[PDB]
Length: 267
Length: 270
Ligand SMILES: Nc1nc2c(ncn2[C@@H]2O[C@H](COP(=O)(O)OP(=O)(O)OP(=O)(O)O)[C@@H](O)[C@H]2O)c(=O)[nH]1
Ligand SMILES: Nc1nc2c(ncn2[C@@H]2O[C@H](COP(=O)(O)OP(=O)(O)O)[C@@H](O)[C@H]2O)c(=O)[nH]1
Ligand SMILES: [Mg+2]
Image (cartoon, rainbow over all chains, first blue to last red; front, top):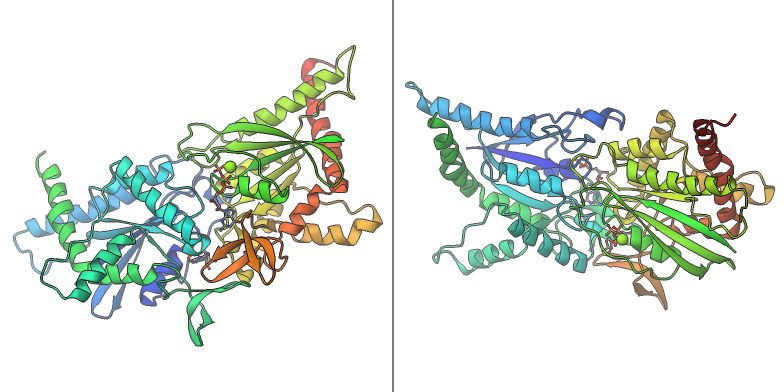
């Protein structure tokens, strides 16, 4: 099964570090890091990488340059035209007479990383999310969760949800566990939805914690553990993605692609 | 007994009001800004207090809404307009026939604290553009905000990339004085520690057997006045009477004189 995940967010939020933390990949060996003088008028670029994880083929669609430019002069075009190009390619393939094994390149999920350093959503965040929330499944993510205390974390989560309601942003909603699964799957589902949006911490480094060498971030005053749910929501994000991959695919096909198909097939 | 005018330039919610309250060990009443301001607004607030045995008329100037707009081309203009306005009113005082320079309230910006967001890469596009517009008008002190975000290894390399970028782009930042031999070595390490990695907090956490201003995390306690944790104590040394006087003198003898030459020749003087 194919799965394409798009990553969008201000540069320097730990995006690459979190993504590699999810599946222990090295998706960014050669990485163009421009100077400040260079990113004054930096265009948004699409960089896609495909890796096999256990088993499925995972594609990460990164968007370097997003937010770097001083001005935004259609800074969403390259991203939107990419999303539409994958829709357009699927429609052309499934419409062919000798369609055979169809390679699904449609974007199934878009992680939008939100800065923890502000009070909430910036106008660029709202404009972009409203620009693609009818095209892809938006998963808002609070990057660098270790910059927030627990009370600051609760406030930022509640406010982001309220501003999403305020601007009528359509984000991916986890399916309610149909009254058939175990009590375990029922509790996990309402727990994941109660922690949205996920505030996460990524790390490519080993630290000592509770007498074990685990991934995390080291400070003079303490250690942040990646896999500690009492520190950040990394496990809740990773579990959410794995257990809901198929549903993200299904909503992509049934909602966004069909809406694209109609919105195009007429004229 | 003199005035001191601090300009705070940073992104919305970066910790500007907190760091001000932490520097002066008080709380100035300010309101949390939103991210949906159409333009950058310059908002000054004057306070009468004593810091380091000085009758201080402190004005804290905040560039409200900085970094929030989708399009930020001319974001520096309201900041330069304010700085130039204070140079202008001062020059009008000098050009008066019947003057009153000793009673005049000096409203010129003496320090600009430029909060740099702790991304961990180099400088943002808005930081480079704005500092290049401000470096010949104010004494810029670059600081890395919310430095309790950056581990010590990342912070070391982060400072180098920031300073390296100011050098290669030619951004003149303030330098603590090295002339007087008594404060030569100490100011040498103050300049060497730029940009200051600061942490602001007015909440008091009990550490050991003392209430210390700090930030409480599930994994630890970041002590504001711990110099192993951050550079707050080093930054606060700008508020000693010696450094305040030097920041005012550079303002007058360098930045204001450059403005003065431009205005007077514009006015027609030779
Ligand atoms: N991690 C971390 N958080 C901080 C630090 N200083 C302040 N904060 C938090 O950041 C939030 C922003 O605080 P403010 O100082 O009011 O924000 P601001 O920079 O004044 O920006 P405006 O609201 O537009 O005036 C506060 O809720 C603080 O709890 C810091 O040093 N480190
Ligand atoms: N405080 C904090 N810093 C992080 C975290 N994850 C990554 N970083 C640091 O942020 C810096 C830039 O991270 P990077 O993953 O390259 O950001 P990206 O540009 O969004 O891909 C690096 O120095 C990381 O070590 C986190 O969860 N918390
Ligand atoms: Mg404030």
